[PDB]
Every structure is written in structure tokens, then in C-alpha cells.
Length: 61
Length: 53
Image (tube, rainbow over all chains, first blue to last red; front, side, top):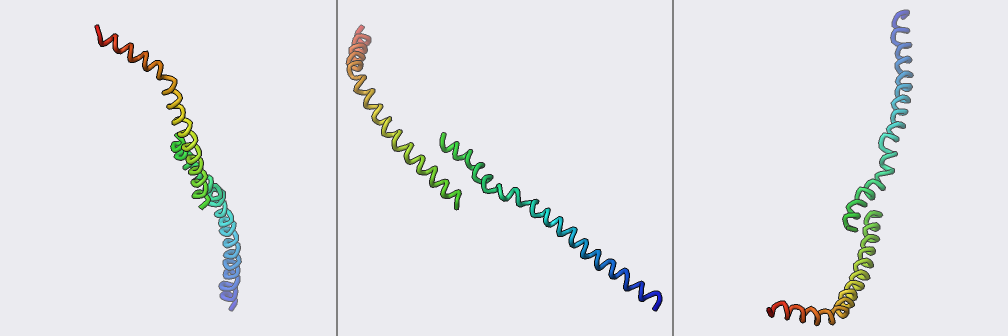
């Protein structure tokens, strides 16, 4: 009782709540994963328009 | 789809440019031709003397 009631309770709570904290950390890195593609794929519109603007400039020539 | 609409815009630009510039150039060629005719008579007279030595 004396050994196991602490040897399986407290560390389990610690890993359990640190698992929620690590979930919050990797969720924050997922909030960064928003930026990881979002600021560029908001531009990808003007990217696929302006890259072909040069071929349209060859069309103007 | 917006890119396709922009392609339609550029296509209308080539429509107007092609049509109006081709009309003006087809007029320019006639203008220069009718400007040349006296000088083509002069040019024929020039060639006649050159080929008659």
C-alpha cells in the first residue's frame, strides 16, 4: 500500500497533466503551423497571377 | 476562376489592340501607297534609264 499507492498514483497524474501541457505546446506549434503555410497561401493567389503576368508580358510582346 | 476572368480581360485587350491597330495600319499602307504613286512613276523612269545604257 505505502509504496504502490504513491508509486502509481502521483507519477500518473504528473504524466497525465504534463500530457495536457505538451498538447497545449504542440497545439501552440499548430497555431504556428497556421503561419507555416497561411501567410504564403494567402499570397499564392498573387503568386500564380504575377508569375503568369510575365508570360502575359511575353504575350504583350 | 479569377485567373480565368483575368485571362478574359487580357483577351479583350488583345481584341481591341489587334482590331484598332490593324485598321490603322491597313489605312497607313494605303496612305503611303497613294503618297508614292508619283514617285513610282519617277522610279520607273529611273529604272528605264538605268537598264538602257
